[PDB]
Amino acid sequence: DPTVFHKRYLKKIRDLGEGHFGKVSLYCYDPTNDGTGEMVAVKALKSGWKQEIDILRTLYHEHIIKYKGCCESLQLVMEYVPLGSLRDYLPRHSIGLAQLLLFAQQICEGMAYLHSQHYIHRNLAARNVLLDNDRLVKIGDFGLAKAVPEGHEYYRVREDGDSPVFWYAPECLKEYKFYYASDVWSFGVTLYELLTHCDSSQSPPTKFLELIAQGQMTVLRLTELLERGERLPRPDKCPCEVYHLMKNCWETEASFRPTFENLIPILKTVHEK
Ligand SMILES: CN(C)C(=O)c1ccc(Nc2cc(N3CC[C@@](C#N)(C4CC4)C3=O)ccn2)nc1
Image 1 (cartoon, rainbow, N blue to C red):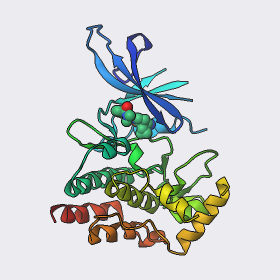
Image 2: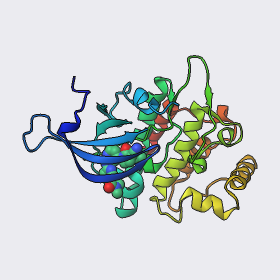
Image 3: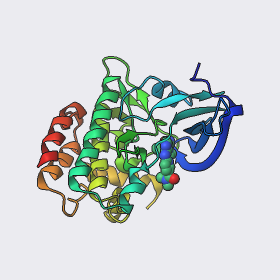
């Protein structure tokens, strides 16, 4: 069973940084001891602590990080994605609008697929979207993901620790309800990060905090100002039509937002123009 990784064939190279609920590292996997082996990414895990594994095991698509197996405190083993996160990539290269849109498209494809499998992500930001060699998008960090039971539209969870509240729709900040439409909001914020080249001083927490204290006063204030209709600003050099898309992803009421399935055509259309 090539889903079962043996400690004895796993040799560490680099730390790769941190995901939600565990460190990630690059390992060589050399079961036949051939001196070359295979590069893999391993996340060290550990109620619902194994949910990341259970969810990702069941996902297969070109725009989601590929599950490889586990090592029996548990280790999750995934494809290594060499270029890393969009958040560290974009500030360090010049990238064309047409290509930022293409990255946007691919996030939507994967998110549409994820939604079709009845999962929500709840952690969609540029820091968690990774790039492979051909600059293909792979969505990552499934630490916060949940299954939405059949014929329900949301899931209720109060996170005990940190979560990307600056990426979260009002219904999530206020009532701890997470809809499919909530990931669409997050994707709107993510679309903003791409267009601001993930400049740190343009970043959502940067911009939101400008308009604003304590950890949870911040959240109540942020909720208040989203409900009043205030939003991140148009990125410099961002086309009008694209700003419209983001604005649509940030409708206050979740039923107004477009779906990822809706977004694919629209992004394809704007990708040429
Ligand atoms: C400074 N940088 C960016 C790096 O040194 C670097 C370069 C490549 C690379 N590839 C890679 C990274 C992950 N990671 C990073 C941690 C995470 C989790 N969970 C992030 C989603 C949150 C995850 O899946 C997974 C598979 N391949 N990673 C890092």
